[PDB]
Length: 151
Length: 150
Image (cartoon, rainbow over all chains, first blue to last red):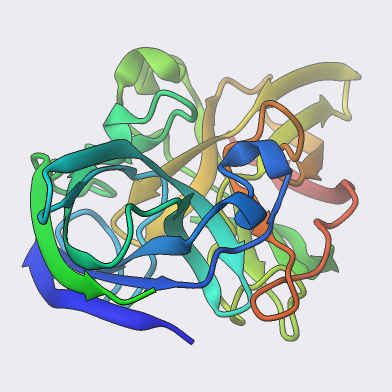
């Protein structure tokens, strides 16, 4: 099943956790690396925290985020980069990416999370009047997750 | 806020419509200014029970393509537009600020389509045997009527 990595972190009014699991076969296939050419599926689980100031109830998935990453193989310095895509699976939506790793050893996953105002595939608005408005979007946050990959 | 017509069970979702006063939004240039509008029109789209696209009952369904056609039935004036996804203090919704055509009876058609699933896709579907979900719903149309007081 899924392997949690690092520790969940409270940032920008959300709880940001990371896991990996087997590569996930995707439709359309061209959205991301094919599962058959990958080692793992990396996943960010991002939910609203209590007293989120952007209109999301505690435990809600936060959609339209821009989630990017740097994955470093600490044993030799190799860095691979990309974006997590939003997607739905049978346990709900998440942000993830199929990746080919660099062999067993110690890895550092660094996530960069920006609010929906930064999405350049899909515009997303925020109410700002007194009656229906919410607080300003969080400024971009980063979170790190270190783990040992076995194969 | 004033409910429009009745919620409808379509495509594995509950699709309701409401209007309220015009809303100020950021980025403001992406929606009709509140001062130039009569109402904010809102589509409330939530997953129903036993949803086949991975959503729990009551979840907001994101990344949909939602458009509308409004007809002032008194005089036949037709108006078309798109909703944009946005968040307000009661959560996310699909909305648009609209200038109407005066008091009277209106017909609202909501066109709800799934996320793109081709080379333009944002939002993917898992399809393997451990994590996969069913196919996206076929596009649906929901019809409502209401009387606008002015």
